[PDB]
Length: 36
Image (cartoon, rainbow, N blue to C red):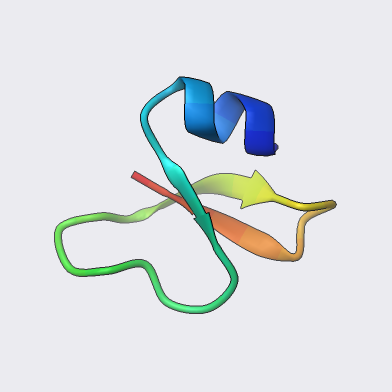
């Protein structure tokens, strides 16, 4: 979720994770990816 994503060093994005990050979980009721 958003809380764990952000607290653990990630960001919530709806579409693509930028280069040198990867999908690790989700945010916003699962509609977005947590990119770390």
